[PDB]
């Protein structure tokens, strides 16, 4: 049984915590729920930590008083098909392997499944750790609660004796690095300096051995990623997001200065040895658009190359942890502003960006976003109970599972079937354009070896490579983005038509150049 | 937002609560969750209460940290047919009127329905208060959450100006008395002496005017009827039960001394 | 009404039958249920048959006393989509036509459907008889009971006047030969010598005119394929299987000598004119792993070519009826041991194997097989009845239709949805790797004409052809195998990664060789 500690004693040294804790809705929640600080209190001074207190980061620390939210979070949506590869004819990107050739995603890229699995899925995907980590057996893939209890309760490491990234199976990659983990867990929140920069007080950083870092991490999507444990108020903890919104002053809604001001973020910095160490972003309001944008964004979390000179940009560089915080039509400019690209296409040699799940940036400017709707309205609605205390569902899943609460409450003119039909109209239309964009990209890509072998000049190949960048960007955004156009159908339409235009331009350029070589 | 109070100061006078609270699973739960004792602490001595502190008896006091248990409790089972009279050919006792003739149950005795309604159903049944109390309208009969929030949020009193038990409709009875309420609520747990005996410190007792008592009561089946708020440990609070089991030495299982 | 015959009279000459019949559970079942032997008994001698007795091979011969088993067998699973071509984007092998080009399966290869249809489906598939046989009309495709009553009750022959294999429609093949029928029916069990070898007493053999043979055959999957009609004990009748397990001494579980000994097979030979003629394999136990392995295996049942010198191996050769009885990683060695391959790829010219439904060999060594689980546990479980005499369901179908009896009885920790999710995780993962294997095989195949035309040497082409063999084998096993990895997910994973490795090696070899030619 827990025994309370005297928080006044802590507050003597922890003024920032005092100011948060005493004012919020956790003012009566004793520190012992999450911290074991006995030896810390015996040894600390006002500027030196002394013995490190233990801080609980398990979600059960919150589930004791918030079982409803915890249970809704950990529910596994069995209809979210697991380990479903996107590069197949029946999934999101039928020609993905040809289009992404040269990139680590060619090894495996599955559709997302329920949040409980995020950390385990990150660890076991074929592109991440060379196949080092596996579930203990193939039955464990169902065990959401187990994954939440801790990744290492359900996973095995092929070689606990080594800590290097290497292939354990031939068709795997070792793309994982420490930045990835920031969107899977915040178990490292006290051990990682802001942005993963080198820091005396940080156990882990962008340049750490990711296998060793992995072994230290257990829990997915900690509840405190969106809720300050001290004030219980809304926040974000993701460094990349704070950096974009606050440090770079882009604001929470870069396209709406007024909304950015009303629904803003306040950066709170915590120090170690009186030197800035870590930060959180306190939100003005409980704005799930910004909470979900901690992870559902396009980002860099990887080494890459400079657009200017093609030189390597390694994990040690700040750019290896970066939120572009730019919609699809501002993205090329945002990548130019940091002088960065992700990979060279294996066939065309083009410098290309790699886009990932840009839901937050896609949502900006959509009809729903403009009308003050937020992710949670459709994906974590309040529960409707005939007789019950209302709480917010933490199931984070498609509104198809709860259309009454997620759509039909606003769309009184529709039945569930009508609303589903509206969704399907958009997704079907968008998917048709994605498929057409891929057809044209693939047609362009296939001409590169023919052009090279026909003696087409490097100048013409480079012209086509520049078009490839744009054709790729304006296509890939939409296979990366999870709503298949729903979050912003007009933007998807304009973008995908732009992709096709670019590819058609490249096809015509290469075809003409090949024919001119043949004629000469 | 709640501000915690200095529980150690309470414990200077409240040794019994200290021994329960500091040992159980509510040792970290501050008194401010259930008591407003500011003026009490200002005026009390260990021998004089001073200002009476306020104690929350609402189930929301527990639902804050125990929403899953509260929500399962308050759910209304619509399949438990409401206001279904047992003295009919299709219910439990087709000849009940003949057999029970001379007893107040002849006026109305329905099947039970979900616990959320126990106090409101007690107040509105035809045999209890002469028809004095009704739901605010016939729609309110569905409102389990409302009844749990408080009986008087969903009921009306035909005559707030009188406190006597009398018939307001011809075929009703006034069988209710203060003892009934002990199986409907424990909102009176600090205002009722053991067994409802007369007591200088008891606002209410077996001989109280039941209508006046009724008006003071709000919540059905308080969570603390089975769970001690201080220790979080299992308990009962019903005097009649404690009297049988302990005072009369019958034990919890009168047919099984080992159990 | 049947009238019993005096079996003692038969037993005077039929000692093997006496020894089986008098001891088993059919000891009270009179011969007249299945044999009309009146004129036989009048004319036979102890060594000469005299008039041939009639033997009933229709399944109704057993259905009279075993209606429950018969009815469960003949049920048509309408959810098993009929005539569903595998070489489409929504089926098992999207790039099958490119990959299998040169082989008869390019004409048509559908997913399997319910067992009642096996013989009719064999007769009507476009790759088998040149389109000679059709259902009487398109309505008859539903008639499982009709097919079971007899193929010729529901099919028509385009030309009853000729018996040659030829095309009746342009896009058909004539791949059928007599060996195929051994996995469709055993109506010929008394007319076919062991292995289909030439024999004086055999009406049919490997070299027979298959159209004439076809016309003599009526019933699918006779009940006596797994149950000896005389002893009622468990057996197999399939020559290829007996030959692998017993003649070649490979055992029923080639990877487990102990299990092979406990769950073994005893070959029983029957003679004609005191010369070995046909054989059965009596099983030590009712082991469905071995019963189903009569057909659900990789086999040769076709002409092919020698790996050594490329010469034709015709139906007359023993190798035209062969069970490799080898898992995917032992298969290349098993094909080398008989010096055999199936076809030359139409584009690459590579000698290639053709793999078919190797469920039995894939199942070996899997977690379930190692734990003593057998096909029937998942595909023909005992019926569960609140009040009823239990019998074994003969419906032979996916456990999805009976998850309570097929999985959940062993997997108490799971709900049906969890178990289905576990299956889908494996199938989704495996299918993603199949698709990737095909992508790489197709990329390799497409380089062959480019390499040939660029002047790449035969030595380099032959190197790539040798890689093609392996890339093909380690892919095709898994489109052939029906569980999409479920029966052995680790093996599927290792194999498919091997396929991709081989293809990538071939792509790199050919690309480099083409570029070197272009540069010269
Ligand atoms: C000892 C019980 C207890 C623990 C442990 C606890 N909380 Fe709370 N929490 C409360 C109470 C009490 C409230 C106030 C409820 C109210 O009045 O609305 C609260 C309020 C909240 C709110 C609403 C705050 C607001 O401003 O609306 C959030 C979000 C919350 N808690 C999250 C968490 C998270 C995340 C954890 C785990 C780090 C956690 N809590 C741990 C008891 C707890
Ligand atoms: C910590 C980073 C992170 C945060 C914050 C986050 N997500 Fe996710 N989300 C993921 C990852 C990772 C997955 C895929 C998990 C997996 O496949 O194992 C995912 C999956 C999902 C899915 C697919 C679930 C399914 O059934 O397939 C939805 C919908 C989703 N997120 C919505 C949201 C919404 C809405 C928010 C804000 C309330 C949110 N997410 C916050 C990382 C995050
Ligand atoms: C900005 C936050 C963020 C970073 C950094 C991030 N992810 Fe994710 N990850 C997500 C979200 C959101 C999802 C679910 C949406 C989706 O998959 O499209 C996801 C899904 C996944 C999935 C399940 C779907 C799939 O792709 O197979 C895996 C595996 C995964 N991430 C691995 C990685 C690896 C490896 C890294 C580092 C190279 C990484 N993640 C970096 C946010 C992030
Ligand atoms: C991706 C961000 C995110 C994560 C992670 C998160 N929540 Fe929440 N939570 C929300 C949002 C959004 C709301 C509703 C805010 C609003 O509309 O007022 C919410 C509301 C709450 C509330 C207020 C009562 C209610 O239900 O509205 C509690 C308590 C809470 N969450 C607890 C948890 C616990 C416990 C966890 C960990 C299992 C958790 N949250 C994880 C975003 C998050
Ligand atoms: C107006 C409602 C609405 C809002 C607001 C909304 N989405 Fe969605 N979201 C959808 C619909 C509809 C789909 C398609 C789901 C489907 O077809 O089942 C979708 C799909 C998703 C998916 C893929 C889910 C799956 O299972 O395939 C993710 C992840 C997601 N949204 C995240 C977000 C995030 C993060 C935000 C806030 C930036 C957001 N959404 C805003 C309605 C919304
Ligand atoms: C501020 C939050 C909070 C409030 C208010 C609260 N509890 Fe609890 N309760 C807890 C915590 C924390 C535990 C211990 C959970 C654990 O460790 O298992 C707990 C434990 C319990 C247990 C389990 C005790 C045991 O020994 O197993 C019961 C029963 C319980 N509470 C009932 C109540 C009732 C009834 C009320 C209303 C009088 C109430 N609680 C008020 C937080 C609260
Ligand atoms: C405070 C007294 C009290 C306690 C303690 C109590 N009950 Fe009840 N119970 C009632 C009353 C009064 C009703 C009828 C309520 C009504 O009709 O409005 C009832 C109704 C029920 C019903 C019928 C519910 C329905 O759907 O019709 C069941 C079952 C029941 N109780 C079981 C229990 C069990 C089991 C416990 C112990 C966990 C319990 N009760 C504790 C007083 C109580
Ligand atoms: C020992 C505890 C106890 C006492 C005292 C008690 N009840 Fe009840 N009451 C119950 C239980 C338990 C139920 C539900 C089971 C049932 O109705 O059989 C119930 C059900 C009811 C119901 C709904 C069913 C019906 O009979 O119409 C009413 C109304 C009711 N009581 C009124 C009264 C009145 C009036 C008194 C005082 C004369 C009274 N109760 C005294 C325990 C009690
Ligand atoms: C005249 C009725 C009759 C006919 C015809 C008949 N059987 Fe049987 N069969 C029996 C009886 C009686 C048993 C013993 C049942 C028992 O005692 O378990 C039996 C037992 C069996 C058993 C269980 C044997 C064992 O050892 O467990 C199988 C398998 C079987 N029969 C298959 C067949 C097949 C296949 C046919 C058609 C070739 C067939 N039977 C024809 C009556 C019949
Ligand atoms: C005589 C050879 C043969 C034997 C023995 C045999 N099968 Fe089959 N099986 C087939 C053929 C041929 C098909 C496809 C039939 C068709 O498509 O018309 C098939 C189809 C199936 C299917 C797919 C059915 C559907 O609904 O699509 C399953 C499952 C199956 N077999 C399992 C088994 C199991 C388990 C055993 C052992 C109990 C077994 N089979 C024994 C030849 C056989
Ligand atoms: C070793 C036994 C075996 C032999 C020999 C065999 N089959 Fe099959 N056949 C099967 C099994 C098992 C299935 C069902 C599993 C599957 O199709 O993958 C099957 C399925 C079929 C199907 C339905 C699915 C499809 O491919 O369209 C046809 C048609 C078929 N066989 C024709 C043939 C022809 C023609 C031959 C000879 C060239 C042949 N079979 C030889 C066992 C065999
Ligand atoms: C592919 C092999 C196979 C075929 C063909 C087959 N069965 Fe069976 N049969 C089994 C297996 C396996 C069992 C159960 C053996 C065990 O577990 O004891 C079984 C059991 C039996 C039993 C024993 C009683 C029972 O239900 O367990 C009878 C009778 C039987 N089958 C009759 C038939 C009849 C009649 C047919 C033809 C319609 C038939 N079988 C076709 C494999 C076969
Ligand atoms: C532990 C249970 C289990 C065992 C044992 C098992 N399988 Fe399967 N089998 C499966 C599952 C699961 C599938 C995939 C079915 C699905 O996804 O609907 C499958 C698929 C099949 C299919 C394709 C069925 C269809 O409709 O798609 C055939 C044929 C098959 N198995 C035959 C066999 C044979 C022959 C054996 C014995 C050598 C065997 N299986 C052993 C569980 C089993
Ligand atoms: C006769 C009992 C039995 C049956 C039937 C059975 N299993 Fe199993 N299974 C086991 C045991 C023991 C292990 C270890 C295991 C292992 C597994 C594993 C982990 C395997 C691995 O490779 O790590 C999965 C997934 C699984 N079973 C699913 C199923 C599904 C799905 C079915 C139904 C098609 C099923 N099982 C049928 C007993 C059984
Ligand atoms: Ca990116
Ligand atoms: Ca073969």
Image (cartoon, coloured by chain):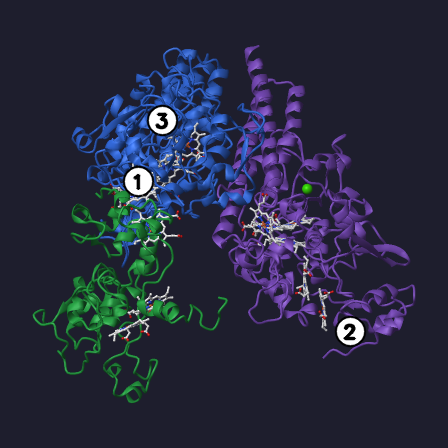
Chain colours: A blue, B green, C purple
Quick check: can you spot residue B94?
yes
The residue at 45%/27% (across/down) is A100
Ligand 10 quadrant assignment: bottom right
In this picture, residue C201 sits left or right of residue A201: right
Measured in 3D between alpha carbons, the distance from the residue under mark 2 to the one under mark 1, in whole angstroms, is 71 Å
Kindly tell me whether mark 3's CB lies below 8 Å from ligand 3: yes
The answer to which image quadrant residue A253 occupies is top left
Chain letter belonging to callout 3 = A
Give how far apart the Cα atoms at labels 3 and 2 are.
78 Å
Look at the numbered disc 1 and say if its residue's Cβ is closer than 8 Å to ligand 5.
Answer: yes
Residue C72: % across, % down? 60, 64
Residue tagged 3: A299
In the displayed structure, A421 sits above or below A459; it is: below
Res. A90 visible in picture: no
Tell me: is circle 2 under 8 Å from ligand 9.
yes
Residue A191: x and y, percent? Answer: 40, 26
How packed is label 2: few (under 14 Cα within 10 Å), some, or many (20 or more)?
Answer: few
Q: Are marks 3 and 1 in contact (CB under 8 Å)?
A: no
Can you tell which of label 3 and label 2 is closer to the viewer?
A: 3
**Farthest left residue?**
B161
How far is disc 3 from disc 1 in space, using C-alphas? 21 Å
Task: Answer with left or right where residue A443 lies relative to residue C218.
Answer: left
Q: Nearer the viewer, residue C15 or A386?
A: A386
Circle 3/circle 2 CB separation < 8 Å: no
Q: Which residue is mark 1?
A: A486
Identify the image quadrant of residue A493.
Answer: top left
Numbered marks: total:
3
Where residue C273 sits in the image (x, y, percent)? 90, 59
Q: Which mark is residue A131?
A: none
Please tell me the numbered disc located at residue C28.
Answer: 2
Q: Are marks 2 and 1 on the same chain?
A: no
């Amino acid at each position: 049984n827990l025994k309370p500690v005297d928080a006044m004693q802590c507050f003597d040294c922890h003024t920032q915590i005092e100011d948060m804790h005493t004012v919020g809705k956790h003012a009566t929640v004793n520190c012992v729920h999450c911290h074991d600080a006995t030896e810390h209190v015996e040894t600390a001074s006002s500027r030196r930590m002394g013995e490190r207190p233990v801080t609980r980061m398990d979600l059960e620390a919150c589930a004791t008083c918030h079982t409803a939210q915890f249970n809704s979070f950990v529910e596994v949506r069995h209809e979210s098909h697991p380990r479903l590869e996107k590069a197949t004819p029946t999934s999101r990107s039928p020609m993905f392997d040809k289009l992404i050739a040269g990139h680590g995603f060619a090894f495996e890229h599955a559709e997302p499944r329920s949040h409980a699995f995020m950390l385990v899925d990150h660890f076991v995907v074929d592109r991440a750790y060379g196949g080092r980590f596996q579930f203990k057996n193939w039955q464990k893939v169902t065990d959401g609660m187990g994954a939440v209890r801790g990744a290492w309760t359900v996973l095995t490491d092929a070689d606990p004796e080594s800590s290097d990234q290497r292939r354990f199976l031939s068709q795997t990659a070792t793309a994982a690095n420490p930045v990835c983990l920031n969107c899977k867990t915040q178990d490292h929140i006290l051990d990682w300096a802001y942005m993963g920069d080198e820091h005396e007080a940080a156990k882990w950083s962008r340049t750490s051995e990711v296998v060793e870092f992995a072994r230290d991490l257990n829990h997915p999507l900690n509840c405190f990623m969106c809720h300050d444990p001290h004030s219980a108020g809304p926040r974000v903890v993701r460094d990349g997001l704070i950096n974009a919104v606050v440090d770079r002053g882009l604001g929470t809604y870069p396209h709406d200065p007024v909304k950015s001001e009303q629904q803003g973020m306040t950066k709170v910095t915590f120090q170690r040895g009186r030197e800035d160490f870590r930060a959180i972003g306190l939100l003005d309001t409980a704005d799930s658009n910004v909470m979900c944008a901690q992870c559902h964004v396009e980002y860099n979390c990887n080494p890459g190359y400079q657009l200017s000179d093609g030189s390597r940009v390694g994990m040690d560089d700040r750019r290896a942890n970066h939120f572009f915080w730019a919609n699809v039509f501002d993205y090329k400019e945002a990548a130019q502003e940091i002088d960065f690209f992700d990979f060279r296409h294996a066939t065309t040699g083009a410098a290309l960006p790699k886009l990932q799940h840009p839901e937050a940036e896609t949502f900006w400017g959509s009809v729903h976003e403009r009308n003050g709707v937020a992710c949670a309205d459709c994906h974590m609605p309040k529960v409707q109970l005939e007789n019950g205390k209302v709480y917010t569902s933490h199931s984070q899943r498609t509104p198809r599972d709860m259309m009454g609460q997620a759509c039909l409450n606003c769309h009184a003119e529709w039945t569930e079937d009508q609303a589903l039909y509206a969704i399907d109209y958009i997704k079907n239309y968008t998917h048709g354009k994605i498929v057409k964009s891929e057809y044209w990209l693939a047609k362009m890509i296939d001409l590169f070896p023919v052009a090279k072998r026909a003696g087409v000049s490097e100048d013409v190949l480079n012209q086509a490579r520049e078009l490839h960048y744009d054709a790729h960007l304006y296509w890939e955004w939409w296979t990366a983005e999870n709503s298949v156009g729903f979050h912003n159908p007009d933007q998807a339409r304009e973008s995908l038509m732009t992709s096709i235009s670019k590819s058609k331009e490249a096809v015509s350029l290469l075809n003409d150049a090949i024919d001119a070589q043949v004629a000469s």
